[PDB]
Amino acid sequence: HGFVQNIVIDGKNYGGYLVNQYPYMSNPPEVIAWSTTATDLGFVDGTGYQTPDIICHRGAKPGALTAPVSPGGTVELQWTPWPDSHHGPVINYLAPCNGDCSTVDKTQLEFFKIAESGLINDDNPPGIWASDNLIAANNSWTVTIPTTIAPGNYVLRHEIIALHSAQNQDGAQNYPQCINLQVTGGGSDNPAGTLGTALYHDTDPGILINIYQKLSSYIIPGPPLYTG
Ligand SMILES: [Cl-]
Ligand SMILES: [Cl-]
Ligand SMILES: [Cl-]
Ligand SMILES: [Cl-]
Ligand SMILES: [Cl-]
Ligand SMILES: [Cl-]
Ligand SMILES: [Cl-]
Ligand SMILES: [Cl-]
Ligand SMILES: [Cl-]
Ligand SMILES: [Cu+2]
């Protein structure tokens, strides 16, 4: 359980959607982060993978604001403290807004995978995962925006999938968090995208999995990584 509280881009902080605060206030601020209704700080499990909740989390709506990113710049997402038990991959996607991200129809977003990290070491099951790297980095993840994609406005869909209960069907816990970015530079690719509701299925080999056994490999969920 947790959420993204802060985003660091080009030497400033952009506050996140504080789902434990803003849903209870009259006058929540405009932010680059999507609003959600996930006030339990929880997840979308496999029962939700073919529902709109998986796109940017339960009840999500676009952020009002969009953050510029320098060409090939970084976006650092800072989480609330991530539980050690919640082992799993960290995955990042972009989808073009083709206009202002604040007015996009989330159900039409076509995401391409720009980064993925999975099982890092398995000397001591259940092992060390990308989520454990995130914890070790004081609950942070750094995304590098590709220089090879067409400039424009994009949604970044940043996600942890916790696998501590994933031995049974619909037991994996997905924690998507979306933010709005303006990508800048000289790239030209328009990578092939996947609708949010087509990213995952509840029988995928990196979804329906017993992490407590020895693992010789791990198939990170979702469509293929884009590399320009
Ligand atoms: Cl709100
Ligand atoms: Cl505001
Ligand atoms: Cl305000
Ligand atoms: Cl925690
Ligand atoms: Cl655009
Ligand atoms: Cl270990
Ligand atoms: Cl471990
Ligand atoms: Cl362009
Ligand atoms: Cl496998
Ligand atoms: Cu949890």
Image (cartoon, rainbow, N blue to C red):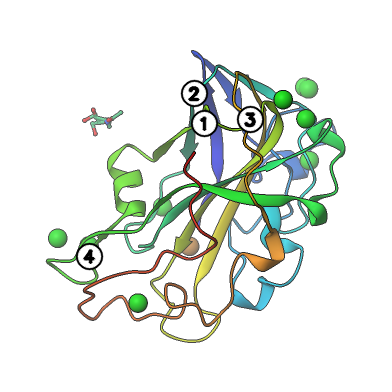
Amino acid residing under circle 1: Ile
Horizontal arrangement in the rendering, residue 134 relative to residue 182 (left or right) = left
Query: Is residue 57 visible in the rendered structure shown here?
Result: no
Q: Residue at x 23, y 81 (%)?
A: 213
Residue type at mark 4 is Gly
Secondary structure type for disc 3: loop
Which percent across, then down, holds residue 80? 47, 43
Q: Nearer the viewer, mark 4 or mark 1?
A: 1
Q: Gap between marks 3 and 2, in whole Å?
A: 13 Å
Q: Residue at x 51, y 51 (%)?
A: 2
Badge number at residue 72: 2
Whether the residues at callouts 1 and 2 have beta carbons within 8 Å, the answer is yes
Q: Earlier in the sequence, mark 2 or mark 4?
A: 2
Q: CA distance from mark 4 to mark 1?
A: 29 Å
Q: Quadrant of residue 99?
A: top right
| Mark 3 C-beta to ligand 8 under 8 Å | yes
The residue at which mark 1 appears reads as: 145
Residue identified by numbered label 4: 127
At x 64%, y 45%, the residue is: 20
Q: Earlier in the sequence, mark 3 or mark 2?
A: 2
> For ligand 9, which image quadrant applies?
bottom left
**Label 2 to label 4, Cα distance in Å?**
32 Å
Mark 3 and mark 1 in contact (Cβ < 8 Å)? no
Residue 24 quadrant: top right
The reply to whether the C-beta atoms of the residues labelled 4 and 1 are less than 8 Å apart is: no
Residue 210 as seen in the image, left or right of residue 172: left
Residue 193, visible in the rendered structure: yes
Percent coordinates x, y for residue 116 in the rendering:
43, 51
Residue beneath disc 3:
188
Point out residue 168 in the picture as x, y percentages from the top left corner: 46, 86
Crowding at label 2, few (<14), some or many (≥20) Cα neighbours within 10 Å?
some
